[PDB]
Image (cartoon, rainbow, N blue to C red; front, side, top):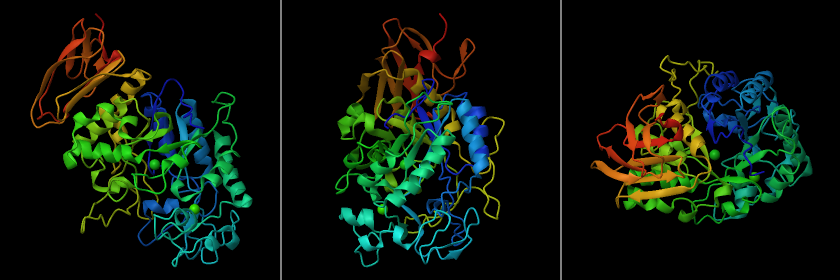
Length: 499
Ligand SMILES: [Ca+2]
Ligand SMILES: [Cl-]
């Protein structure tokens, strides 16, 4: 279950946070397949509440109502059509699985649900599953409020309510059964794996019992004996009584130290310097490489009040962001996931974004808009589409090209200019200092003229952007002025030219 099940040598996945199924499938066919992406993570596809105050926030999709497959992104039929079209062009589908809980205790009752089901969160009644009062952890929690009040306490964190969300009693064979039927339903459709939401809050005991109930993947696209990929949301930045160690044997875990630490590096906070990152990865106390899923930001912390808070980097800070994501994609550590966000009117009041609840671009009526493609291959309507940025999609290719090659040929100027290679397949160079980068380096690469994929690509027998001359000895001179709008350069075997 640590195996991502990627095909065709592809190596990375995007979180198309909040996209409609119909949009994802189109994007699969037109872009993801062609451009070498290994797969998509999609927002929770189950039925969920519709919050009205505030108006239809992104976070409503993390308050399930039933396991019926109709959500903000689409219906069961759209869903199946997407998996299929994405699969047919080799892009896997990973599902965000919300199973720690149902909706909030004060969810009230009525038919305000993504399917228009009826339900009564006051009596803990969810007829569509069905679930009922006895399927919840109330008796097990001993907090005054019945919410998690202290994270120093490992029992609270599993058995109490996460900020008020009704905590499923996952020791119960009935509940374990229900959840698995859900995940199996998805797997049967051709889903490749899961991002299990909220894992810090469930017992590894209960998790294993579920994971063991899951079928092998659909042999329509996946070899026999393939298992669902599992990666788990656990936040651990040190000092936590709860560590990723407890989950790491059940499947992969999110390494939140990765983005947090990487952010303060390119920001240069607390006298952290890029040069320090030669032993980046396990060296830095990150978990074991084969257990890790790594990313710069996710939907939570890109709103500045999650793991890493202020130090996390987002499309809001393009220049640093591109370098950070490029670094991540070049480095061998972890299994990498690129963010794909939408924007919204940020409103900071005492350093908190009072608008961080805002959902995706959408028609009033709270249904989400499609994703329009601009002719120069970017996205309209408030969809950001970082995954479509030249400096990103090209590093996604870079990672495919160099896949497997060792970290090699490290260099640094003692400060915030560094470079490294991956085998003899690729070399990357960063300049995050306040003066120019100016050196000859052993790239470890075959001699020739390579195209800098950051500033463009190889097209025909020429470079659309910068280009770089590697001597037969593999030495190459780099000049990156700190003025440069993208102060880093990358080249690789597939960006080389004929003799
Ligand atoms: Ca729980
Ligand atoms: Cl995550």
